[PDB]
Image (cartoon, rainbow, N blue to C red):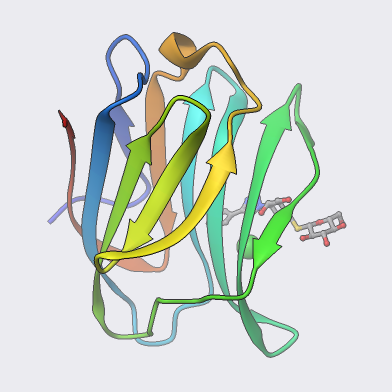
Length: 138
Ligand SMILES: OC[C@H]1O[C@@H](S[C@@H]2O[C@H](CO)[C@@H](O)[C@H](O)[C@H]2O)[C@H](O)[C@@H](n2cc(-c3ccccc3)nn2)[C@H]1O
Ligand SMILES: [Cl-]
């Protein structure tokens, strides 16, 4: 088991062909989860499942620059379930982060922060039991 919030160092930043894998279980009465790919205090890619935003389940993605959030990206598919185990895979591609949950493609997020080799940490927070977090090159 890992302690949440968890920091996964990404030595030398991210690069295309780098695959991040996160395994955990959603807590039974979960409200929120976040992955934060960070460049110092900036958040290059925030991936934020919300289980109860006005009685709707939605994933919000965004970037934080100089402490300001930008334009949110929202789509409707919500593959997480309270109480159940999940796998998140984040593949860095040249133009975007590509995210799959439980082996099904979910969304892509275009790179707004373009100094990929300075995105040197991943924070994992919110209403999960975190089993493992790691990376490999494909
Ligand atoms: O844009 C992404 C951010 O949105 C805000 S909320 C936002 O606020 C605007 C101004 O009022 C409204 O215009 C808009 O409609 C509404 O969506 C949210 O607080 C931010 N946030 C989430 C977390 C967090 C922490 C721990 C675990 C999980 C998540 N930390 N910061 C982060 O998601
Ligand atoms: Cl939230």
